[PDB]
Amino acid sequence: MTKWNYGVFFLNFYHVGQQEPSLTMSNALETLRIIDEDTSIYDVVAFSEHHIDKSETKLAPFVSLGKQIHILATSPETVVKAAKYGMPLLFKWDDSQQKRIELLNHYQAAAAKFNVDIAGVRHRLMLFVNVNDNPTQAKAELSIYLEDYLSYTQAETSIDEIINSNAAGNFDTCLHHVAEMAQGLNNKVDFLFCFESMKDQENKKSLMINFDKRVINYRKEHNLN
Amino acid sequence: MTKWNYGVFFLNFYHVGQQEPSLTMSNALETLRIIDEDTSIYDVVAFSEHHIDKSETKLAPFVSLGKQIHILATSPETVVKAAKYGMPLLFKWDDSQQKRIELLNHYQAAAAKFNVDIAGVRHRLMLFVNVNDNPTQAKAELSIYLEDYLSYTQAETSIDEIINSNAAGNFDTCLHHVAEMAQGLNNKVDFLFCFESMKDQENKKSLMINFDKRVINYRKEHNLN
Image (cartoon, rainbow over all chains, first blue to last red; front, top):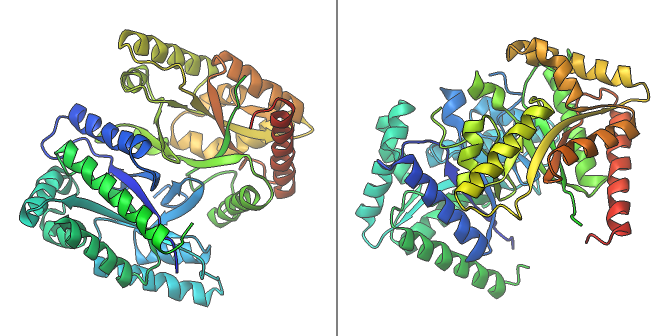
């Protein structure tokens, strides 16, 4: 079997959740502290900043995760290019799951044609994660968090789809849904989670630690280290 | 004494050196291969893409190097903000060395005021590196490489300054100049090198390997591991 890797991302947008940018900033810095001090599984950090270019002269939509260069899966066109060079993809949190699957299949078809071996290649899937004992409250909090971003990207009507393709609900449902989406992507995805839509910093911390512990135990149980 | 760290960056711009983007791409992929297969010191990879925003809604000019978040040193204003949060800087290759020094000093002054300890903090300095037995040829190659980028950023007249604040010349002069610029920045900088202005892929490889070997030997000689 295969070890799944987990990392964290932050949405690089100044207006989220009706928060002052200074609060959004201190919240993000606590996430970083939790990564540094309280946990071990969160291997890499990235920033979601594709709302800018979308809003051309780039060599490619490159995203560096450590020293492994991914291509952000921005279009069928873009993933064909990534496959030509055998590079792993980064799937957008703001794409529907069906769309990500479509892009994965475009990619694997392109690699075959170009005789590019992609056997070992593992992609990364960006997901927002909001855990609440009341699932409606989790989805509500994520919706409110994303309001200004979606207004800026002119994608307000895609909010329900975004909610459905990310992880918002109680803890067990979120984990199950994460596993379902991985399964949909042929279990070829590692993850980047964004926890910032959880206002309650103690809840965020508890989540990040609980998940850290679950992953450590899983890896021990299955001898993945 | 302190271990200096080295990484690599690529300029995310489609028109360099009058090269077809496919060639620029295959050149970059060979650099990645050299990092992966022929050397060990190149710890992280980043992309220079600040020609875009410059050409606002970001929470900050964040750059992730692994899981260590840097702030791109885009203005005195921006570095004061980085110091408030005690975060390390990424110095621009396209800034003059005097400018980088000014920004370093702005930063250290801000941290003192805010009682933020920055003792352990190490920044990163982006530099183009072009080594040629004929120093004029190295500077010439770098100039031609950057022509279209500088036209796009409307900074054509800054080319001489850029040459002077990066490493272009014979191998020993480049290394000495890198050391001088570090010294100017109080020896508080690790590095990201961009090797892509060297057209000759064999010369690039030889350089990357020779430098790798020099750093390994240095670390052994001084017990830095």
